[PDB]
Image: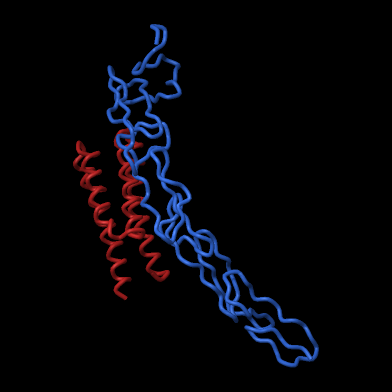
Amino acid sequence: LNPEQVAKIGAAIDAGRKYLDAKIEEAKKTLTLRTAQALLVIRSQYERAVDTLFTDPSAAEKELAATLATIDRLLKEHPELAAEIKAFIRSTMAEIRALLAASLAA
Amino acid sequence: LPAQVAFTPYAPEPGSTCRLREYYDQTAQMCCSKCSPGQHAKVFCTKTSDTVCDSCEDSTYTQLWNWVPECLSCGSRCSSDQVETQACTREQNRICTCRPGWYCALSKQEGCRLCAPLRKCRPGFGVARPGTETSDVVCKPCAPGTFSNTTSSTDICRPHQICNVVAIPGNASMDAVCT
């Protein structure tokens, strides 16, 4: 990875983290604190799933699956919100994986 | 506990806060027990039942007295490039860091998810900005009058020696030789 690729990869990771933090702040502003608590857990698993792309790529798809299952489980009673978070996290991880594959292929 | 001492869950009297190990739950409108570090709220309190706290499973944690519905995931195990400066336990997250001579290319809130070796400025080049925990060394070519004869992440461009009668002039990678 050259500095340009790392910067693009970091920007994608920050986008997912910042989206999750905004969803937490939104749950706090609307006083849906039990949802804010669930989002903290989902954020922690997102961070682990991102870590694994760099520390152990052979585990990445399993950690992504565990992220989406955690969203499904914790937000089972808020399906609209659950769909928004899965879609942001899926799209974010697709972009990071795309940048990684493109750098390893050069 | 005797009849004198209120148990959770209870509604706090006007002018009160909840006890130290309690939080005010807005859904029950009651003071309810928090769970300890290493546990989480398996079941939230209601108006008639207290929080149910269960232990975190391996590779998850809670660092504070809490009422999260599941424990948080530890960060992934460190790669061989990194050093694990804090272990994952049921009460604390894993922290991975970079070795001396390396910087953190992708930083986490705590620690690092990707380390990279610091650049070394070759002879003729000196350190312009030193490396930091999260940033690579920046090099510069040595301007006339200065030099660097080493390959190094810390050595800077240093002045040529002064002398009136030059046998061999100095350049960017070697000192002047004086007669």
In percent of width and height, residue A96 lies at 30, 61
Task: Give the image location of residue B32, x and y in percent.
Answer: 35, 22
Q: Residue at x 37, y 24 (%)?
A: B33
Relative horizontal placement of residue B92, taking residue A40 as reference (left or right): right
Q: Report the front residue among A83 and A64.
A: A64
Q: Is any atom of residue A79 visible in this view?
A: yes
Establish if B61 lies above or below B174.
above
Q: Residue at x 35, y 18 (%)?
A: B8
Q: Colour of chain A?
A: red
The image quarter in which residue A56 lies: bottom left
Q: Quadrant of residue A76?
A: top left
Residue A88 in view in this figure = no
Give the quadrant of the N terminus of chain A: bottom left
Quarter of the C terminus of chain A within the rendering = bottom left
Q: Give the color scheme: rainbow, by chain, secondary structure or one colour.
A: by chain
Q: Residue A68 location in percent, x, y?
A: 23, 48
Identify the residue at horizontal 40%, vertical 69% (top origin).
A4
Q: Is residue A91 above or below residue A81?
A: below
The image shows a total of numbered marks equal to 0
Drawn side of residue B162 relative to residue B95, left or right: right
Q: Which image quarter: residue B115?
A: bottom left
Q: Could you tell me residue B64's position as x and y percent?
A: 42, 34
- Figure colour of chain B: blue
- Considering every residue shown, the one lying at the far top of the view is B3
Above or below, comparing residue B50 to residue A1 in the picture: above
